[PDB]
Amino acid sequence: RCELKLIASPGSWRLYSARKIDERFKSYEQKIFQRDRYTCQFCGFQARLYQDIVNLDGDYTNNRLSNLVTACCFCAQCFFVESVGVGGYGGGTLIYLPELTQAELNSLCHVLFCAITNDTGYKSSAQNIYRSFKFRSQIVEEKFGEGTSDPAIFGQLMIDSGVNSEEIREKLFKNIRLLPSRAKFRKQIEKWAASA
Amino acid sequence: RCELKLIASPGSWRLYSARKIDERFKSYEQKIFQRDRYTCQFCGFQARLYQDIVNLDGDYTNNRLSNLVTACCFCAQCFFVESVGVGGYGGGTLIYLPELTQAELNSLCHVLFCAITNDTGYKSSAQNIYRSFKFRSQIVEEKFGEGTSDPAIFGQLMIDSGVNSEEIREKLFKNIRLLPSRAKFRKQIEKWAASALEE
Ligand SMILES: [Zn+2]
Ligand SMILES: [Zn+2]
Image 1 (cartoon, rainbow over the protein chains, first blue to last red):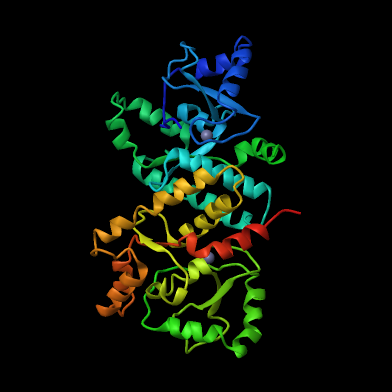
Image 2: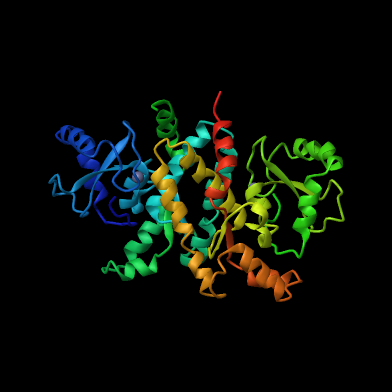
């Protein structure tokens, strides 16, 4: 699969949003789901519903097929951390978890949530993990500032303190992951349980 | 819940095993299961099959019901690290995990093996994450000598060194977790993944 990184681009979500509503694109997006078999190119989540498309280069003015790839809503919100929670888009909380990368985290969240709605006895051991990962939101606060566990604030943090190198910006924010909220995605989860 | 902690007791397994094969224990063995609702008191795993009963305080000359708690076999083998692999009991490999407790790693392994047994489209994700933890085994051997990722060797080594107290225990076991091997538990894993369907 491809690579995942927390990105806080300034005015890029405007283009990602304006493109998704632009009906010239609603024919391109039907191609992009099929060329990738409706599978997220980051964690592998495969579902016929509620899939998004993100640019790998970050520039949403270029639209060549080699750039647009499929991504679930858990991974799509990683390209716009500054907007996760703005006007209803996305939902989650930043946590400190070195043991898992971002892709392994999201693909694990799909298994947990699916094993929570489809209560199979494993709903117990699943909630005792999701809340356990949600507990790391305090550690992110004792390391960057009050309320910086909210992705809307942290997005403006890494935007204010401008760091251009994808190397220092990496070592600084190392071991910080975006844990997608179970509540803000209740509709996608339950509809994925049926469509199976 | 309670507090899960890796323990290298001197010979409590020879007592823990000798009790499990006793008829006087099997009588009220059901009461502890009925009390804790067939749920592990360390990682919250619920199942009506292949559950263990351990003593909290590590002493097996005390058997009051207020001490015997229900523990899944993942957490149960953490009270006998020196026996993991001895006599065919349990299985696993010690790894150096930074910020993740044992009770969280155990409950995490349940979810991964349920995605390996019932390959509903998450087997690659479940295997790749499990192999990410089975790699931290070398970090342990780089801090205690060769072959110390094996819990039967690492366990007996620290028994041969005089580790008797409790606060020394927490120091030498700090940020060390016992990752149960999926191969050594396939029988109980499939039994769980099958009897854990919807309705
Ligand atoms: Zn994804
Ligand atoms: Zn347990």
